[PDB]
Each structure stands twice: as C-alpha cells, then as structure tokens.
Length: 179
Length: 177
Ligand SMILES: O=P(O)(O)OC[C@H]1O[C@H](OP(=O)(O)OP(=O)(O)O)[C@H](O)[C@@H]1O
Ligand SMILES: O=P(O)(O)OC[C@H]1O[C@H](OP(=O)(O)OP(=O)(O)O)[C@H](O)[C@@H]1O
Ligand SMILES: Nc1ncnc2[nH]cnc12
Ligand SMILES: Nc1ncnc2[nH]cnc12
Ligand SMILES: [Mg+2]
Ligand SMILES: [Mg+2]
Image 1 (tube, chains in turn brown, green):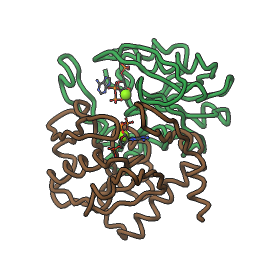
Image 2 (cartoon, rainbow over the protein chains, first blue to last red; image 1 turned 180 degrees about the vertical axis):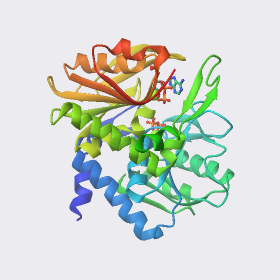
Image 3 (cartoon, rainbow over the protein chains, first blue to last red; image 1 turned 90 degrees about the horizontal axis):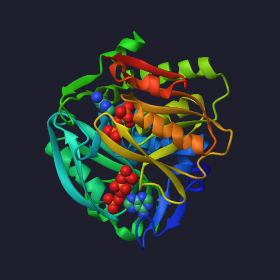
C-alpha cells in the first residue's frame, strides 16, 4: 500500500445526504488544507501521466470549479498550460456549450472557441468522478474543438455509479475508489 | 520581465457578462506555463517578504480564486482553505451575501475551516468593487481568524476595491483603471 496514496485517502471526509437525500458527499477540503496531502495528490497524478503519455501532452483541462483546485498545480508540475472548461455563462468571447447531468443535478459546461487548436493533446482533470456526466460533457466540447483527449483523471472515483464505463473508450485514472 | 510575462497574458472583452463591464480574461495566464509560474512566484515572494513565517493558511475564493490559491499555498508550504459560493460546501457553515461588479452573490465557509487566532492571506484572481473579497474577510472574521492581507492577480483601480478592504493590506500584480 503506497504511503503517498494514504496521505490523500486519510484526508477525505464524508457527509451523508448532501446536497440531497441519498448522496454520500466526499469532501476534498481536508486534502487542500493539508499541504502534505495536496502535494501527494498532485505528485501521484503527475507520475501517472508522465509514465502513461511520455510528455506527449499539450494542455491540462481543469473543470469548474473543484477541478480548478488541481488543474493548474498539475499542469505546472508537468510544465504545461491549463485550459478552463467552465459552467455556462462564466467565460467571455465566442464559446461552445453542452448540457449534462451529474450525480445530484443538471448543468451546462462551456469552453472558449480558441481554447485549443485542432490536433492538440489534452488531459482532463477533475476532483471527483461520479456518473461521469461532467467529464463526458468536457470531452464532448474538447472534441468539438478537434482536440485529442488522451485521458481523464480525478482524485476520487465512485465506482458504483459506473462513471468509468460512461467515459469509455477514453482512458480514465483515479487515485481513490469508493463505492 | 517576470511581471511582463503576466502583463502580456491578459485579454479584454467589452460588455461581458453585461453591458458596462470590461471583462479582463485571465485564461491566457493559465494557458502559458511561464506566465502562471511568474505570477505565483511574484505573489509568493511578496508574501514571504511581507509576512515572514506568520501565515498559517491561504484562503482561495470560489471559483477563479481556486486557480491560484492552492498553487500559492504549495509554493509557501501552507494549506489552502476553501471559501465557496453558498450551497456548495457540506457540514455546518457560515454564509454572507454581497454585491460584486456585475451582480449579487453569497459566499460560505465551513465552521471548522479555521480556529480562532489563525492567520490567513486571502487570494482571488481579480479585485473589482472589492465586494467578494470583503465578504470573504467578513466570513473569516466570524471565525475569529486574523486576515493579514488580501492579494490578487488583477486590480481594477477605478472601482476602489482597495478602499473597501482598508485597512487590510492589499497587493495585486497588475493594475487597470
Ligand atoms: O461525475 P458526475 O456525476 O458528473 O459528478 C462529478 C462532478 O460534480 C461535481 O461538480 P459540481 O457540479 O458539484 O460543481 P463544483 O465543482 O463547483 O462543486 C464534482 O466537482 C464533479 O465535477
Ligand atoms: O471585486 P468584486 O466586484 O467582488 O468582483 C471580483 C470577483 O468577481 C468574480 O467572481 P464571480 O462572482 O464572477 O465568479 P467566478 O469566480 O466563478 O468567475 C471574480 O472571480 C472575483 O472573485
Ligand atoms: N458524491 C459526491 N461527493 C462529492 N462531490 C460530488 N460530485 C458529484 N457527486 C459527488
Ligand atoms: N471586469 C471584470 N473582469 C473580469 N472579472 C471580473 N470580476 C469582477 N469584475 C470583473
Ligand atoms: Mg465539479
Ligand atoms: Mg470569483
């Protein structure tokens, strides 16, 4: 058992029935508050991506909002820029947008039309994968820009919600798996 | 020239999200690794110089504040606490309503985010009217935290955000009218 993974796992805390009945909410806040834990999370993700893609990445894409907490740090670790995929209405200039559902509601994601040029290689990062709706919407938009999505990564994966399978055949990797 | 790497990576869009606003887009700073690194480094060096070893935590403001908070905290060897838009955080919370340049909103913080006395520097991407950053200071004030300083990448000086935070020290890398 990797001690690095334990530093992350030990800092996840759970709240039942938030924000709606029957949801078991995984709170990442303690990971951010513990510098040792955050550093471990970024390092583990970066190690995976370095080994899996050999540096052949152009940009990291961070997902509004909790994905914002990991995107830039991960990109910086890898020497890469970070592109923003945001909740609809937040980004200026020409955009594309897509509707989707997540575990406990629905929303719309959006990306600036000039965020990526055709052919550019991207890895998508978010804090947690659940139903995979949010990540799938991100992949759909990056596809509209003719970007190649190499992989999607998160800190946490809720495997009972089968988000992984929803993303196929786009590869996926998480640090931690809960039901 | 480190500052110029940041300066060169701000775009502007008139009348977004509403008429009368000139929107400063930070996307290009994030997209250019050298730009982003320069920004974090400039912020970190300022804070180390100003506060020595007296900062306990960085607090980053949902959402665009999240882009800088964790990086800045990591650079300084500190943890980052989250101040989120109301409704987003689990557990017992405090919240406060406020006006920003182009709308109204509400921020929230977890009651156990901080212990009384602990010293915090608040980070956000951009300071306009100062309403957001002020609301964040209020929330920290209710937890009896000591807010040492507020910082941002961009400051819109004609909106007098600095005066709303006074006498709390404020520092920004870039200034526009
Ligand atoms: O796999 P899914 O079922 O789509 O759920 C996962 C997504 O939902 C949450 O975001 P949320 O919409 O709560 O916004 P936030 O990031 O601002 O918390 C979470 O941060 C993921 O992005
Ligand atoms: O100085 P003020 O007048 O308060 O305005 C500045 C704030 O407004 C913007 O946030 P916004 O509410 O647009 O949400 P976002 O961070 O998700 O873009 C920006 O990110 C600052 O936090
Ligand atoms: N169960 C959960 N916990 C935390 N964030 C989530 N986003 C979607 N589902 C979630
Ligand atoms: N003029 C502006 N540009 C970008 N972000 C902002 N947040 C508040 N006012 C803003
Ligand atoms: Mg999210
Ligand atoms: Mg903001």
